[PDB]
Length: 281
Ligand SMILES: [Ca+2]
Image (cartoon, rainbow, N blue to C red; front, top):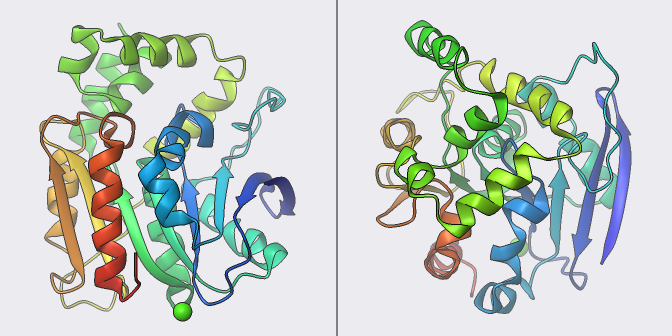
């Protein structure tokens, strides 16, 4: 259980490696959403007992985006934070530092985009992808206008929260919502989070086309909550991928962060995803 760090053209990235050496399986590599880090995004899911049972036969690499890791310094003012594409270009350095040749990528939101871009760049290194809340399209001008309007009366934390959770959830104000409102609003590194939020917002098209030559070439499990902010984007993404290689898990009752609210169902789906990939799980 070791925390590492590597220099890349776009700065250093921190990552934690877990598990016994498993040379004949891909590494499970994770990448978290805006506002979160591995701990606030994925730890509840990966510490879930049923998930522990599956992952014991894999090595796991948990990436913290630059500036998001525990105890990260706040970037100086004017820092040019890497674009999502530049974040995907940090991953070869992580894998070569580790001497790993293939991965199954598991990502949420911004993290799902980053891993999908990584896969497009390096498709022989990616055996499968779990993509939670992916929006593979650039922000359209209509959406930009509505976002800038919203930003006139909402703070950056409130806006990151509307990216993470449904509006029903946030007015519901459950104990998970209050906990995450507090996490983000009072984050010591909130200024770094804003930079990543901006990169998210400012992303380009991934450009999937069904029967196209810009496609993912591995199994993919698309995950989203019914009525959650990214439902439409994930539904649309599904329509652009190879249906024989793609499964779509639209979870009722899960909300904006399925990996936080339904780790049990998500773990069971992962199990069958791996079996469909040809791996005993
Ligand atoms: Ca193998």
